[PDB]
Image (cartoon, rainbow, N blue to C red):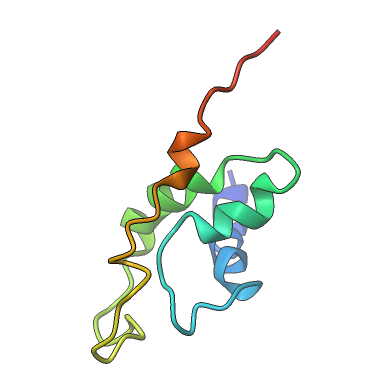
Length: 84
């Protein structure tokens, strides 16, 4: 039951080992994990996101956003997994 607090830092790694400077959205963090085949940060990060609920003025985005307009949806285009 004490493991619930151990994950509190896990969600931090998704941004601790990346360049959140410009960006600040999911997918990226899941990329480094998907490099081998992992795929949890997707729903995991989002699940904990609502829990952590970061305060305002912590978006790290003055008045710029390009990666958010590019609408990168090429990932779904390669969606066709299959078990067994």
